[PDB]
Image: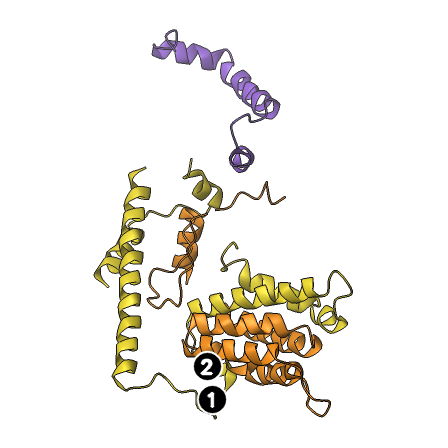
Amino acid sequence: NLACHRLETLLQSIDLPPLNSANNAQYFLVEEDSRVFSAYQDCIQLQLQLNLAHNAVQRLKVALGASRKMLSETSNPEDLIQTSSTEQLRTIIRYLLDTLLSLLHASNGHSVPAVLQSTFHAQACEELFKHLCISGTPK
Amino acid sequence: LRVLDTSDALKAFHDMGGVQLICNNMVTSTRAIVNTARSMVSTIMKFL
Amino acid sequence: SIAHKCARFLALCISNGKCDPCQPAFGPVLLKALLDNMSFLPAATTGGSVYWYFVLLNYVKDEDLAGCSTACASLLTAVSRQLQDTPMEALLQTRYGLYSSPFDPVLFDLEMSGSEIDLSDVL
């Protein structure tokens, strides 16, 4: 919390001119970059230890005799999608795009089913790019 | 710059209509030469 | 461990499919079971478990293509409208090429092999 907080204060200590992201890319080709790099390194590493420790304590608590979170039969699929971590969301997206690519190759280059071809209309395609390209990983 | 050090130099420059001619030079020079400075295009082409 | 053992046991049940003429094949029935269990994927707990689940799905999807496609499409819609739900992370991504969120503490799994990406070779 304190390291990530200092990182937050560090990024808040960046003077912001009128937004010209060309200059933002120009900054690649300064001590500020190294110090933000170090602060992010500490914050992300500490997250890594925190995550392994949480996984370890969950494993130990389960081994003690306790049980993990149970999926109730009354659970709405949409709220548990909403109450799922974004990292879980990105990972499962990557897996299911792998699955969809497997289906596409599974057609062996033949006709893709027309159901998804009709499904990938203008608005759905636009919405998926609009939601992923701004925020998703490059991969 | 050196020949315009004295006040009388400026006064004579105004007297014989130098300022109108220099302003005309501004219009012609600004209208004439196109910028050659490395713009955004060069920046975006640098990393390609 | 339990998920991997279960995957192995179902694979064995696939391997010995010398079913009787009155005995239906194991493929379609397991497939509709995975289709039934599709809805609880975002509520899962373990990356390796769902990984093996996806391994089985990837192998057995040859039996039926329409149902899995429409179900995954619904998943696409849902998780795409959900994923978009702060400027700081995007700022870090743009200014420094640094993608992973530093404030969100929870991670799920790690991928590591010893072998940005230049797409010129990809082109």
Q: Secondary structure at mark 2?
A: helix
Q: To which quarter of the image does residue B6 belong?
A: top left
The quadrant in which the N terminus of chain A is found is bottom left
**Residue C78 in which image quadrant:** bottom right
Q: Which chain is yellow?
A: A
Left or right, C54 with reference to A64:
right
**Pointer 1 indicates a residue of which chain?**
A
Query: Which hue belongs to chain C?
Result: orange
User: Pointers 1 and 2 in contact (CB under 8 A)?
Assistant: yes
Q: Amino acid under label 1? A: Ser
Colour chosen for chain B:
purple
Residue B20 position, x and y percent, is: 53, 19
Q: Is residue A67 left or right of residue C2?
A: left
Q: Is residue B13 above or below residue A104?
A: above
- The foreground one among B35 and C18 is C18
What type is the residue that disc 2 sits on? Leu
Q: Residues within 10 Å of mark 2 (few under 14, many from 20)?
A: some
Question: Against C83, is A19 above or below?
Answer: above
Which label belongs to residue C14? none
State the residue position of label 2.
Answer: A80
**Which residue position is annotated with label 1?**
A75
Rendering coords of residue B19 (x, y %): 50, 18
Q: Which of the chains bears the disc numbered 2? A: A
Residue at 52% over, 58% down: A134
Label 1, label 2: how many angstroms apart (C-alpha)? 7 Å
Which of these two is toward me, C28 or A46? C28
Q: Where does residue B10 sit, x and y in percent of width and height?
A: 40, 13
